[PDB]
Image (cartoon, rainbow over all chains, first blue to last red; front, side, top):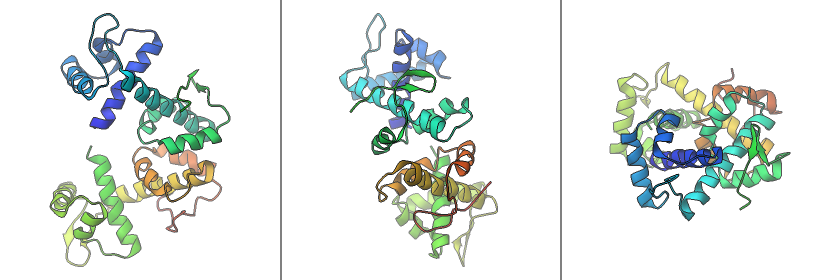
Length: 134
Length: 134
């Protein structure tokens, strides 16, 4: 899904960086059950919408308007997998693979809801941090 | 994609049904705001794998199996409202529209974990009895 697939790769770009690593398109086609060929359609499209820029070293640069939005999918991602865990108590194992889906359907007003409602924001149940204070 | 789309279709054919409006496509075009030339593409397409029938009385008449694919999506639909209000808190006239998203993610794994976490799973916010339950 276009809008959803931007979020999907903008999610891996954050996830590599935090992992400590260069957001190199290649890296992503082993991350994703995907290919170079398609991966360039996505970072070609994306960059022109203004989200990522292709360069050398680590290579892929999320723009000012690239960060603020994957910062979001990711806290959306780190806050729903906690609602599925802290509140419903989902088996764990399911929790990420499933919160990879609630991260697109969750809303900003439901975030504020979960900020007044959870007993620890801070870290994903897998430890490691949840960002957006906006 | 088009699986959550037959999950919208079966959810209005089942909703109109439940409210008494007999489900003749122009109502499906109106309720789902895509047009009716758009809606026969999809009603007719959900029929190739026998989910609906077009026939006099009821005009759309969803099969032993499409009706399963409707009762489900209406059960992760009422249960999402019951999350959204009962453990979260979204105003209320905001709560439907979120669950219309969440009725497509929300696994079996998840609303079965929900029924042990809510203290009245027989209610809807919006009157309507929660269909499914297993």
